[PDB]
Length: 200
Length: 200
Image (cartoon, rainbow over all chains, first blue to last red; front, side, top):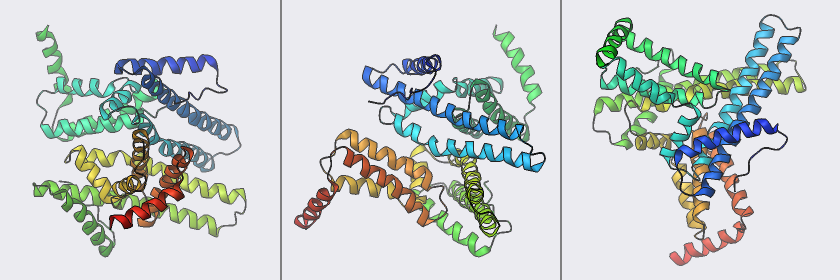
């Protein structure tokens, strides 16, 4: 079985992660209830693993801010805490889909990544296509590639806010790309507003 | 087009990376020659990007070793250089398959990852199954999952030696797993030797 890594954690926190993980698994509609429990625990354990990494990051950052360090000494110490955090994300990133692949196919693994990132890939992709119906095939492919990338970082983020901000950076990249390719995004939005009304 | 990031690099080094990248692409048998050139440059550029990251890591490590620092001061400085390196790998890891996905399907992206890691996934998987014909399905799935994980790290390694050592760590993990599940690996190897001879 996959055990839930709940030892020495606040029960209210454990419960919140278990229920969050269960809701993601429910959407998969798995027919084997034991497999569904194992999947649920792999997901819950990743949430806890990420929490522990950010707790260390925050403790380091607080100690630096409260220390004497002042200039580049300070800022380099802060950057070093962030690098330590990213190195922990890197070292544990690929183990998560490896564990899920014991139980799930590639499509289900993607549904789990979407569940953890609030389905922002699909929502953003469809909204972009709705607002710019003239997009070339190659543009749709590039836009979709950057949203998939964004999701790899967002699934590792600390909380809902940081997840949305991670997608925000790639959405900015999408906009710069479209403008560089001659699209007038202000105008595209005006015409979409009009399409929305006429569509009624 | 994808441009090759060759500016200000030694031409002999550039040529070595271009030829290495070309050999990987040749194995794909792509029918569109312009697409094959773009793919070749995305691969070459990843080699250069990795090289630059390790050059910074090595320069930092050398300066620490040559400095006054001695105890935990020294060792923490060394660990901080390694964390900076891992953070650069993390930040650029997901951009590589995003770029390849502009040109390639998922099967071809996997062939590129295999090309960069000397096909060690398939070789190791098949050898393991050849040496232990009694493996359970669930064991084959676990073994394969760890080799896929290993490949994500190996493709980011500095050179051939470090690639083989990365797979070596996961092969050690495979062995510990099989022994924990009651397999006697010394005996399995003896019987395989005998199977190899009788197989003639």
